[PDB]
């Protein structure tokens, strides 16, 4: 059957639920920022200035 | 993108504008506002593997080599699941709830364009005309949202790729354009690039094999159309987008390994990786579907 | 020599649909592989969102 | 204009001062572009006398 | 193809794929299925004369 | 302790174990148990001035 081993991500404290197996790991920053798309003008050079 | 440790990743989002005029003798801090922020998340799935086992007497009683070819079918069985897992994420950006259909109010939403009833469009030359007609209305929806005109793609099955080649033949069109009749190729159509995919409505991997070589599947393509569901298996005709709507995060990459067993006199070969998938921008996506019966 | 026409990206694609191999009789004034329009009666066509 | 506080700039994991300065000079070029196209529809509503 | 002596010929055939998720604790030996083989045969007909 | 950015910190916790005898011919995997884990948290309050 299965192999006995360690549970490094499960929380097995006193009086604490252990139904999640990824509770002690952290969330990290990806490395890219989603900025809005740029806008451009069209009438800059089509009249008298 | 790639990371080193952790169970998730984060992408920040921001955007706004401003502008008023100030009378002489006023303060700038009486008519001030701010810009808004939000975020997105993508989570890792797990570990995916494949292996074979070979004995030493059957490898000596045989007349052709097998070892070098078993390692070529282990590296392409893992590259097809990651290809069907991404095409199922472009059909869930289009099923978002109405009250949460865009990132920041005022940036844009997703487009779902209908073609017509299936009963009426019976001839295979009556459907390519509609498909071509609806690719000029989907070109004006990506421009109202300021999407750049540099990388646009359209995905469809090989069955609907031959319904556009039948509407540009001498029996249906007035003059020659686009296609090549001697080889069967289509050039760009309004800035799009046409791609045919034999495995479009197949999802990701599972947890158990079948008899042919049966359990919980991840990234399943939606099955039945309903009130809150717009894209399903019984509606889709194609998908179009810009290359900024879907992303991938890698923790570990592909690798091969070898091992020798002495208690059973054999050899073993394994391959594995770990990845995650998700969607980012709702305003760079769309779909073509059949009209309700 | 300097005349211009301004319209939205919605009514700009209705002129592209009327010069297609399914509505017209011969080729004129457009490029089907990119979606561009040349000059029309000495005017210049501009799309403004 | 824009205002940035100091306590909130120490808990953050990326830089924001570069993008705030690009949306300021781009928001002042769209008003001048849209105010010219509104002077062509006023020439058409002048009174009859 | 051309042969020098014998009464038949043989062509081998093979091919298969697929991979699955492994939860921590399970064994690779309990989810193993192999790739299959088969063959094709072509025989000499005889002597044709006129 | 000292950090550089964030809104809180983490401290992990661990347990203990014991040893046993092994006769010649027995396996180590039939007498195995595990060690447990948990965590603790501390948060930042704000800015204090004079």
Image (cartoon, coloured by chain):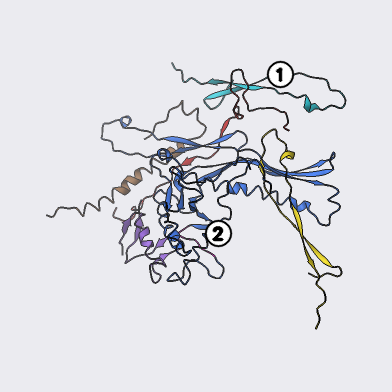
Chain colours: A red, B blue, C purple, D brown, E yellow, F cyan
Q: Can residue B137 be seen from the camera position used here?
A: yes
Q: Residue C11: percent from the left, percent from the top?
A: 34, 57
Q: Secondary structure at mark 2?
A: loop
Magenta residues, start to end: B185-191
Q: Which residue is mark 1?
A: F16
- Determine the residue located farthest toward the top in the rendered image: F50
- Note whether B132 is above or below E35 in the view shown: below
Q: Is residue D38 left or right of residue B187?
A: left
Q: Tell me the mark number nearer the camera, choosing from 2 and 1.
A: 2
Task: Return the residue nearer the eye: C2 or E25.
Answer: E25
User: Dot 2, crowdedness within 10 Å: few (<14), some or many (≥20)?
Assistant: some
Task: Return the residue nearer the eye: A46 or B293.
Answer: B293
Task: Return the residue nearer the eye: B12 or B70.
Answer: B70
Residue B103 figure quarter:
top left
Q: Residue E8: percent from the left, percent from the top?
A: 82, 66
Q: Residue at x 80, y 47 (%)?
A: B54
């Amino acid at each position: 059957a299965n192999v006995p081993g360690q549970k490094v991500g499960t929380d097995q404290g006193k009086g604490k639920s252990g139904s999640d197996a990824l509770a002690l790991f952290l969330k990290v920053f990806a490395g890219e920022v989603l900025t809005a798309f740029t806008r451009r003008s069209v009438t800059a050079d089509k009249h008298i200035v | 993108r790639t990371i080193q440790n952790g169970k998730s990743a984060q992408f920040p989002v921001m955007g706004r504008t401003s502008g008023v005029y100030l009378a002489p003798g006023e303060r700038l801090s009486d008519k001030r506002k701010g810009i808004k922020h939000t975020e997105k998340n993508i989570t890792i799935d797990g570990l995916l593997t494949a292996d074979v086992m070979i004995f030493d007497i059957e490898d000596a009683m045989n007349h052709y080599d097998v070892a070098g070819e078993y390692s070529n079918q282990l590296g392409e069985a893992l590259a097809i699941a990651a290809d069907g897992a991404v095409l199922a994420e472009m059909a869930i950006l289009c099923n978002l709830p109405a009250a949460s259909n865009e990132n920041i109010a005022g940036l844009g939403t997703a487009s779902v364009l209908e073609v017509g009833k299936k009963a009426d469009l019976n001839t295979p030359a009556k459907l390519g005309e509609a498909i071509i007609g609806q690719l000029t209305i989907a070109r004006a929806k990506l421009t109202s949202n300021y999407v750049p005109a540099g990388d646009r793609y359209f995905y469809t099955t090989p069955d609907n790729y031959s319904a556009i080649l039948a509407a540009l033949m001498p029996n249906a069109a007035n003059y020659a354009a686009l296609i090549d009749p001697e080889t069967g190729n289509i050039r760009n159509v309004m800035g799009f690039v046409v791609v045919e995919v034999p495995h479009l409505v197949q999802g990701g991997a599972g947890g158990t094999r079948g008899a042919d070589g049966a359990s919980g599947q991840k990234h399943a393509f939606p099955a039945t159309a309903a009130g809150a569901v717009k894209v399903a298996m019984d509606n889709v005709v194609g998908l179009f987008s810009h290359r900024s709507a879907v992303g991938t995060v890698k923790l570990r990459d592909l690798a091969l390994e070898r091992d020798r067993d002495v208690d059973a006199q054999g050899d073993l070969i394994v391959g594995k990786y770990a990845m995650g998938h998700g969607g980012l921008r709702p305003e760079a996506a769309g779909a073509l579907v059949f009209s309700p019966a």
